Length: 267
Length: 268
Ligand SMILES: OC1CN(C(c2ccccc2)c2ccccc2)C1
Ligand SMILES: OC1CN(C(c2ccccc2)c2ccccc2)C1
Image (cartoon, rainbow over all chains, first blue to last red; front, top):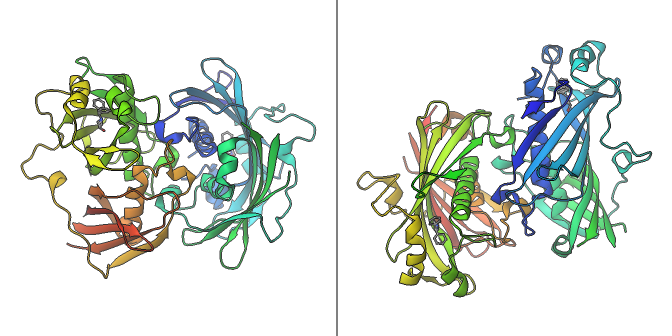
C-alpha cells in the first residue's frame, strides 16, 4: 500500500482469500468491510497517526474518533483469488466530524466494483461524551485531506445521507442471543465495527441470501455492544429488488445499539 | 505465493492486518490458523486440485470422497506483530492407508528465524454418508507425486506432543462458556463451519485473566463431529497443571462430543 503522488489519498491491493468468501465463491460484505477498515488504518499510519488513530491534541485531551454511520454499495463482489484495489481518503465536515470515503476496483479491468462512505464523530474515551471538532484538532489533520470536495457519493439525495426509521415490534424476522467471542474484538478489546454488520445480516432469512445479492447496506452506530452484552437482531421487509429495515438491540432491556437498511437484487 | 524449486512444498508471505491482532498487538492463534488454511488451499490449487470448494483428486470426485481434519496441532514461539511479514512453508505426506498429513513452518521474513510450526492429520470421508475410510491405492497414486518421498516432519522428536492421546474431560468442568452458535462469517464456501471457529470456541472457556497474563504456546485439537449451522455448543475447560488445560466442546442439548483438546500457556 502507498499514498498517491499528491499525498492526499491512499491505495492498497488485496488478494481475496479462501476463508473470506461465501457460497458464491465471492468476498462477503464483512470481508469487504474488514478490507475498508485495514486500508483506513494503513492510510492513518502512513501520514503519522497511530490502538486508536489520534492527533497529538486528541491524545492530550483523551479524545478518539468513533463511527456514526457506515454506507457500502457493491456492484460486483471480487472472486476468491482475485485482486481488488481500494483507494481511500478523508475530508473534514466542519465541526460535526470527519468523513472517510473508499472506491473499490478490479485490478485487472480497472473498473469500479464498489464504493463506501463513513461518518466519524469525536468522543471523550473515558466519559463517552460526544463533542464537536476543535480548531486545534482540525488544524492537525486538514493538511492530509483534499481541500476541494471529493465525494464517493456525489448524487443529489443519495442513499448514504438518508434518515433511517426505528423498526416497530413485532419484527417479521429475528435472530436472538447473539454474543461476541474474542475473535470479534479489536486490539483495544472493543467489539469490531464489522461484527455489527454480521449481526444485522443474521436476521435475513437464508432463502433471501441464497437467491439475492446484497447491493447496498447503510448502518447507524448508536451505542457500543460490550464484550459481556447479548444482542437481538430484528428485520422487517419494507419492499426485482428487496429492501429491509434492521434493528440491533440489547437482549435484556431492549436498548438500541444499531439501526440500518439493506437493498438486495434477485440473482 | 509459489511452489519451491523442487515442486514438493509451497511458500507464501502475509502482512499481519490491524483486525487480525489481539490486545498484545500480535496475531491471534485464530489468525495464524486461518493463514495455515489459506496457504494449504493455495498449495492444493498450484498442483492442480480444487476450484469447486474441496481439495479432491479425479477419483475422489467420482467416488464422492473428501478430506476432513482429524487433528490440528500448533506451536508458536513468537506471534507476528501488526504490520509484520510472516512467511509460511507447507507440504504434505501420505501416511499409508490411514490418511494424509499436512505440515507448516512459520518464519519472520526479516530475520529468517522459525517463529512457529504446525501439523495436521486428515482422513478420507464419503461426503454424503459421512463414513470414514482408508485411502485407496488409486487415490494414493494421484497425490504421491506432489509429496516428498523421504520423511519430512515439522515435529520429528520421539513421542512429541502432536501425537499424544487426549482424554475426555469429566463433569463438572472448572470453567465453561455456554450457548455458542456460528454466524454466517463462521461458515466456509460450502456452508460448513470453518475449522478455525472450533479453535475460537475452545479458547472461549479460558478465563480472561489467563489470556491477559499468559501467552498461548501449544494447542492440540481433535475433531470428532462437525457442528451444523443450526447447532449450539458448550465449551468446557479444566486446569490440569506454565499452565495446561484440558478442553471439551459438546452440543448444548444432548452433550454429543464435537471436539477435545489441550492448551499449554507460558506466564508473560
Ligand atoms: O475516520 C476518520 C479519518 N480520520 C483520520 C485521518 C484523516 C486524514 C488522513 C488520515 C487519517 C484522523 C483524523 C484526525 C486524527 C486521527 C485520525 C478519522
Ligand atoms: O490436507 C491434506 C493435504 N492434502 C493433499 C490432497 C489434496 C487433495 C487430494 C489428494 C491429496 C495434498 C494437497 C496438496 C499437495 C499434496 C497433497 C489433503
